[PDB]
Length: 218
Image (cartoon, rainbow, N blue to C red):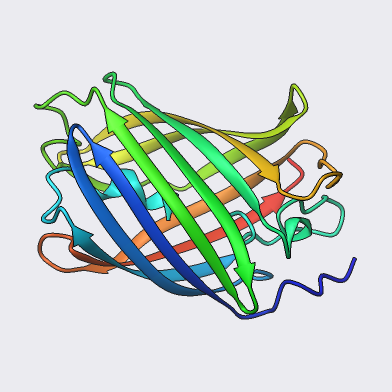
């Protein structure tokens, strides 16, 4: 099906407001992406609350599954959600008891996706890798997409690589909901993801972020 609303080159604008372990912040994003290649990049700037007193990496997956290369034999719920858009809500449950809830309301105005992002985190141990800024990157992942009680859901076993050859596990569950009624739910499938901070200044007040995502049947 031809997607009139999804241009090969799209702009991306974003505002995140959040609070992690009591620390408030606002972060702006300006980016571009190629929905049919499953690739996007974004320049992020912390606008309030910097220097952030926790690992920037916990935030990065909150900075849109439109940017995923879908084969023709899998229903692309995300590209089919436009022009009206969709929203998602995600739990990030970390192995040491830290917990985040993130939400994004995604709209489209012309060639630009807009993102209203909220990020709440709590219960991170003060001595843990998040509050001590010991993370290096997220490992590449595979999201399992399926319908759970009528709602499109993505589950991911994620891991942050830490300093010293260690990993720090986090389980994602994301629910995805189109704004238009009657958008056809897809069959179960997978999305491979790789997210990377390409560059950052010393205290992560400015960050360049990149993601590549590809859907597959199994």
